[PDB]
Structures are given as C-alpha cells and as structure tokens.
Amino acid sequence: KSEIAHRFNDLGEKHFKGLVLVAFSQYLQQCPFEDHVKLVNEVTEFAKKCAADESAENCDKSLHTLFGDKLCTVATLRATYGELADCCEKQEPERNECFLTHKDDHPNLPKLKPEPDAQCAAFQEDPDKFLGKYLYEVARRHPYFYGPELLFHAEEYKADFTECCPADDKAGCLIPKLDALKERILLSSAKERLKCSSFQNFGERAVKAWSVARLSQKFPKADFAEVSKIVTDLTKVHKECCHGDLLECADDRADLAKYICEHQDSISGKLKACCDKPLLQKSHCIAEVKEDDLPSDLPALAADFAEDKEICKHYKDAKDVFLGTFLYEYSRRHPDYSVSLLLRIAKTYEATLEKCCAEADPPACYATVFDQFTPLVEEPKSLVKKNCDLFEEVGEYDFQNALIVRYTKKAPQVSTPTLVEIGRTLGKVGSRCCKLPESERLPCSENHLALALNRLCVLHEKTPVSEKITKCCTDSLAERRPCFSALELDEGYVPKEFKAETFTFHADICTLPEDEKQIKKQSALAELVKHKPKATKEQLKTVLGNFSAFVAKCCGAEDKEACFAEEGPKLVASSQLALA
Ligand SMILES: O=C(O)Cc1ccccc1Nc1c(Cl)cccc1Cl
Ligand SMILES: COc1ccc2cc([C@H](C)C(=O)O)ccc2c1
Ligand SMILES: COc1ccc2cc([C@H](C)C(=O)O)ccc2c1
Image (cartoon, rainbow, N blue to C red; front, top):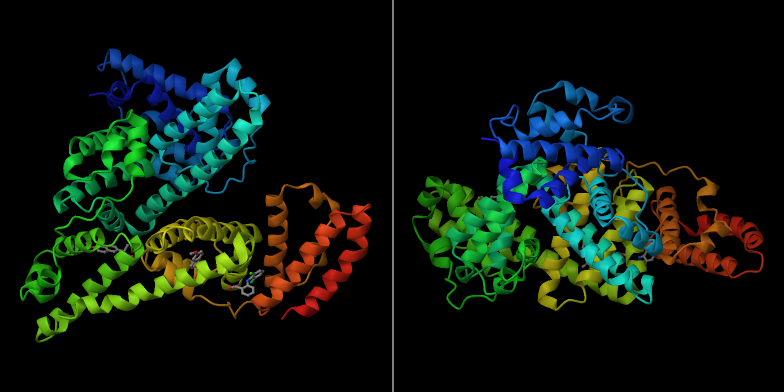
C-alpha cells in the first residue's frame, strides 16, 4: 500500500535514515550537510506518519515521487544546480532519470584528511551527527557507491574512533586505520561503478553474464539453477542501487543474503563464516567471500559442448540458456582465469557455433571449438607475467611511471591529472596482484584493470577528448582491456607546445608528503610526453631521474629557492635535448 511505510518497517529507522542520507548526498552532491539532514528527517517523519496510517494522504505515492519531490524543495537549487532545476519540472520516471544523468563522477572536492583531535572531539560532542557526516562526505564523492555497503563502512569508521579516541597514541592507532579504510572505500567505489557502468553502457544481459562467470568461479559446487537464481536476484539488487532506488536495493539485498545462508550447504562451504554474522557484516562477507574448492565431480565438457550432434538445434532452440550453461561450466572450473577472459571465451564459443551451424557439416567444424580458446588464454597470461616482472624489477613508483608514459602516448589529449590518477591506479594493480600465488595473478590483474579502465571511461564520459578512448570504452565490455592494450602512440597528435613553467619547480614541493611529491613529478612526466611523444621510455626515465635528483638536492639545500632558481632552468632546457 505505502512503499515508504513498507521500507521503513523492513529496514528500521537507523538504516532507513542512513540510506536516505546516502541517496540525497549522491543526488545533490554540493548541498551542505545540514540541508540534507533536514530533508532526511522530514522524509523519515513522513514515513512514520504513513507507517501509522497507510491511508493517510500521499502515503501511496512512489518513493521517487516522494524523494524527488523532497529534493526539489531545496533552497538555492537553481543557483547551486543550474542544470537540475529543469529536472524538477518533470514527472517520474523522467525526473529521476534526469537527476541521475547529472550525477558528478569527479566533483573534485577537498581530500578527506584525518584530523584525529578535531574528529575525536566532534565524534564525542555528537556521534550521530559525526557518522552522518561520513556517509554524506563519501556518498557525495562517489555518487554510485553501493548504498548498503557504505552503512557497513560507517560501522568500521565508528569502531576506528571508538578504539582510538581514548588511546595513548591517537594518530598511531587512527591514521593507519583510516588510510586503509580509504583504500577500501576507493576499491569498493570502483567495483560498484563498473557494475553501474555495465548496466548503462552495455545492458543487463552483460551484467548477468559477468555475474554468472564470477559467481560460478566462487561457488563452483552450486548447481546452475542456484547460480541463476542468485545472479537474477543480485542483478536486480544492483540495478536498483545503480538507479538510486537504495531502499529497495537494501531490502532486496537482505532477502538475498537470507536466501544464500539458508542454502549455504548447497552453495559453498566458505559461507559458514559469513552466515554466523550480523546483517551488514554478513552481506559484506558474502560479497567478498573467497572461492570454494573445486568439486571432485566436475563434468567433462567435450561431450555436451563439442561432441554432441544436436548442439546446433539446442543452441538455436535457446541460445542464452545453452550459452549461459556453457559459461557456468567453464567458469566454475576456471578460478585461474579472469572474468573478462571467461566472457571472451564464451563469445568465441558463440561465434564458433554461429559459424559452424550455418556450414554443411557442423559437428566436424565445432569439434575443435575448445581449441580456439588457447590464444585467448596465452595473451593475457603473458602480459601479466611481463608487467609483473617489470613491477618486481623497478617497484611501484617506476611502474606507475612506465604506465603513465604508456597511457599518455595512447591518449595524449587526456588531462594530466587523469593520466596521473590512472597510471597510479594501474600501477597499484602490480602491488596488489604480483605478489599473490601465481595462479591468482591473472584473475587479480584483469579484474582490477577492469576497475581502473572503467574509471578512465567514466571520466572520459564527462570530458570526451579522444575517439580511441571512446571506441575502446564502448565497443565491448569484454574486449576493453585488450582494446586498450592494443592502442599505440596517437600519431595524429600534434606535440603540445613547450611551456617552461610546467617543468619549473620551487621550494613548496619540499614540504609535501612523499605521495604528493610523486604526483608533482609524475605530472611533469606526462607533460614531458605530451611535448615529446616519440621519446622512448628509457629517455623519459633518465630525464625524470635528473628531475628527482634535482628536487632532492634543492630540497636538501641551505637556500632552497635559490637552488631551484639557479639549477632548474638549465635542467629544463637540457632535458628537452635528451628527449625525442
Ligand atoms: O615503460 C616500460 O614499459 C618499461 C620501462 C623499461 C625501461 C626503462 C623505463 C621504463 N619505464 C619507465 C618510464 Cl617510461 C619512465 C620512468 C621510469 C620507468 Cl621504469
Ligand atoms: C548468454 O551468454 C552470454 C555469454 C557471454 C557474454 C559476454 C558478454 C560480454 C560482456 C560482451 O562484451 O559482449 C555479454 C553477454 C554475454 C552473454
Ligand atoms: C600485473 O599488473 C599490471 C598492471 C597494469 C597493467 C596495465 C595494462 C594495460 C591495460 C596495458 O595497456 O597493457 C596491462 C597489464 C597490466 C598488468
């Protein structure tokens, strides 16, 4: 009768409010914290009235009518959000559709800097307001963050402050915890964005195919029926969340988590751990759960997928099922392949049946179908071993450097901050994945690269600058990585005009944390490539070494700025000669 009552009742006041805060922060990213709290409280008050009497006026309206109406009350909307006021003239679903379309993936808000005294203080004078603020700050920075999971991370954030605010060493307890929480936020943000990007750019059939492969790897003892059931339900969950319907998404997620733990015995022995937990931790745990051991009765596949004479009829009679089945089977036995590699193999199997079934004798044609997968598998294994060798020889900083050079050559039109962010994220894939046991390196690498490349695509959507990127981003989800890997120096590119200030450093740099020093150096590196696109990697590496050396010296100096001022312009001129 009243959706708002229903969700309120299912979720309870705490989570209802939390989720409704997230929604509003993500939709209206610039509004101050206080406006949002007020709007939340109001909606929540409405919900309570409806829970008391679902016949009451307007209680029957949809959530989005209700929430969309609420957002359209904010003061200074047309000033703050010029582009959004027009959305408020529209009805639903056209309205919500407009709000979504204008969500910002790179609002470039200030970085969230742990300030342990000020924060423990604010925490103590009002913990409820302190945690709301966290949800708000994160939601706003990541307008597609998986709602339910943000509530989860908010609990971890509360545990952090609970533990550390009364400790001997406040920052010793707290700054590493919050640094690791921020890594976990960024990674989770990037996983969820890929899901919503997959719905937007490729459709639900693409999200389902990804999720069949992934969950078949994770739960290889489950049967296909069960995998499909979970994938169907998980797909709806994310479709809701990616469409800003967070209350429905949370409720539906909890139903799923219950389902999974009721049937954990016929799903995976790894879920026991997770099913013994409170709600949000449980959901988090199932979502991140490790892959089960491979059953001893995995069926040989030749017979059904290469040898049977009826394949062409079966395939024609129901393509999506026959293929989904193939994908389930192949993926469950292949936790050692990435999801994209599995999807590229499925598309080749498909392509082989399309080809062979239109020929005179299909069975002799499709008899060698499994053999066409060999090169699909070797290419990425070889790439991962090569980049991991490099990573291990040179370390994170220089691997990031190598990737920054790589990406600037491929897309020299992209802004420097994007190239640097992206080269740095790509480089961290080496740190995450290369040290893992070797059978894990390919899946770790490609699954994480999908997250980084999607980020590039998402930023590119905002600020299109290169047709090569557009094409790689939109042609084929499964082929993205190979498509990006194949790009080379854009030759059409006119070297960017030399501007000496760009390469000109000052003593300000000396006071930065290491991190931020690297970014400054890494930004100059991209600029060196834009101006000398044909310089080799070996030349850029030497020239940047000379820049680091110079920065280290001048920062070690008696009179830092005089140092920078005398030595710098010479290095700037001479380094250009060392390039292309
Ligand atoms: O770029 C690569 O693929 C690897 C490579 C090999 C030899 C020398 C330098 C580089 N990369 C690289 C670059 Cl392009 C700049 C600074 C530091 C490094 Cl390690
Ligand atoms: C029913 O079977 C499938 C199998 C593989 C698929 C792969 C893809 C990828 C994401 C692609 O890039 O096209 C999509 C749909 C698919 C459906
Ligand atoms: C194992 O570690 C990595 C890290 C970064 C990588 C980037 C690339 C890109 C897509 C490339 O353009 O080749 C490939 C492989 C990679 C492996």
